[PDB]
Amino acid sequence: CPLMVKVLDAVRGSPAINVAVHVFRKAADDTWEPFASGKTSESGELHGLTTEEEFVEGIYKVEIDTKSYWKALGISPFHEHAEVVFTANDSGPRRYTIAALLSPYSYSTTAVVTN
Amino acid sequence: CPLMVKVLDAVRGSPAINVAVHVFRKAADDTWEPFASGKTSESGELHGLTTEEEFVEGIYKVEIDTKSYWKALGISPFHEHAEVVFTANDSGPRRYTIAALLSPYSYSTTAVVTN
Amino acid sequence: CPLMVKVLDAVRGSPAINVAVHVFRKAADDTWEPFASGKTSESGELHGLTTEEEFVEGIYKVEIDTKSYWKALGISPFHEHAEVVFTANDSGPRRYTIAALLSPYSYSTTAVVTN
Amino acid sequence: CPLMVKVLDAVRGSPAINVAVHVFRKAADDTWEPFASGKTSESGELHGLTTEEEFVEGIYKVEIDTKSYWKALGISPFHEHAEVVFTANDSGPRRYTIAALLSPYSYSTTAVVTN
Ligand SMILES: *C(=O)c1cc(/C=C/c2cc(C)c(O)c(C)c2)cc(N(C)C)c1
Ligand SMILES: *C(=O)c1cc(/C=C/c2cc(C)c(O)c(C)c2)cc(N(C)C)c1
């Protein structure tokens, strides 16, 4: 599993469940092409977005739909989404975990990159 | 000043100086139009991006050029940029401060919205 | 002002107003001696804790009374307080800003150390 | 496993490995008593600190020895440690994950609390 997304809720102290995630890959013409999508599980995790074969070198954008999440809990939040934009695999295949910690007017994101 | 950007460096414990910032407004055709830009000061701040008159309700994107900042310090970073996307809503008088705290593989962002 | 504390609220998108802050210095017997205290202002800031003369090298603890802040907003929080413990080192002239970004189950803290 | 600690490195984009963690529990006389200790694994995780039987209601302090960690990588960091202080089990047994994301002059911490 070369690309995993983990989302936590800093208000509830819980995984952020049923958070929609859209992944895009920049195409040769500099447009964002849809790559993969899914939603976080009861553990706040999203696995199975892509495969080692399909996850080639490129610039990827991980869009985490935080506004839809907060709205469903009665919070009118600040951000539309949290966007994580990075070059992947440019020194060969790596495994990437994109983690996000959400609050209504703030978020933090990190990456864990393993060989 | 309706819109200020503040950038801090979590590796040096300092303001993040000379960081390029680009602000975009979402157009009717759902494309991102350039709106304002500049470079953070010696205090990590960027003021004077826009005016009360021009900063109407809409969806805005603040792109912080973190990759060039880390490259200038000789540190390999993860992200291409940090992106903060939000709706500006006129409910009363308000000032938006977008703050970001940068690390090579992580960032934190918050909004300080005041009257 | 050698030592300033700044507190932000990640749920409201605001300064964290009227937060009690206690500063301690580590004594020779390895106990924490009260040093300075106060409450954040309407801008989330606490100035005037100490002087250049009194703020000598040593180990300091900044305790931020987050639990009382969340209780006053009717929100169940995780932590008893947020604690920032650091050594003050005289290398050149410097000002320490301790910043904290609060959520009910999370906090972020950074140091901005300037000349 | 009712108390787990997870530590990430925001500079390297990796688990924070071999981070020492000390847990204390406030005694009736308001002193901190040693409760448990250990170090993070190659995954940045510390399991097996306590048992459901021993982890009774109380105020706990999780001290993460971040200064020792950074010093071993050639970084003179700001903080002495990251301290996470909380009341545990006061509505019955819960499972607690204390997560921390480290930078030289900053850290973020959150808790995931499950029934
Ligand atoms: C898996 O990698 C993982 C990660 C985390 C925590 C991530 C995290 C912590 C903090 C303090 C942040 O600011 C960010 C952005 C991420 C937790 C877990 N759990 C819940 C076991 C797994
Ligand atoms: C003014 O608004 C301001 C803000 C801050 C710090 C911001 C900040 C801290 C932490 C811990 C974060 O995680 C985030 C995202 C933002 C500091 C200052 N200074 C430098 C006076 C001013």
Image (cartoon, coloured by chain):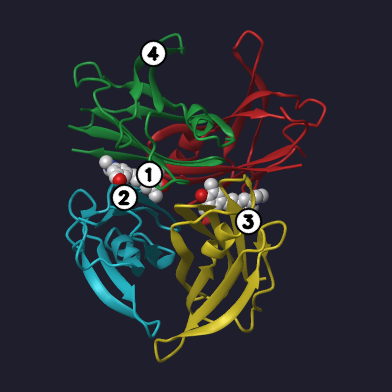
Chain colours: A yellow, B cyan, C green, D red
Q: Residue at x 60, y 57 (%)?
A: A7
Indicate the amino acid at tag 3: Ala
- Asked if both marks, 4 and 3, belong to the same chain, the answer given is no
Chain identity of mark 4: C
Q: How far apart are marks 4 and 1 (CA)?
A: 29 Å
Residue where numbered disc 3 is placed: A16
Q: How far apart are marks 3 and 2 (CA)?
A: 27 Å
Chain identity of mark 1: C
| Secondary element at image label 4 | strand
| Secondary element at image label 3 | loop
- Residue C14 is tagged as 1
Residue where numbered disc 4 is placed: C34
Indicate the amino acid at tag 1: Ser
For disc 2, does the CB lie below 8 Å from ligand 2? yes
Residue where numbered disc 2 is placed: B8
- Asked if both marks, 1 and 2, belong to the same chain, the answer given is no
Indicate the amino acid at tag 2: Leu
- Tell me if mark 4 has few (under 14), some (14-19) or many (20+) residues whose alpha carbon lies within 10 angstroms of its own: some
Indicate the amino acid at tag 4: Pro
Q: Nearer the viewer, mark 4 or mark 1?
A: 1
- Asked if both marks, 2 and 4, belong to the same chain, the answer given is no
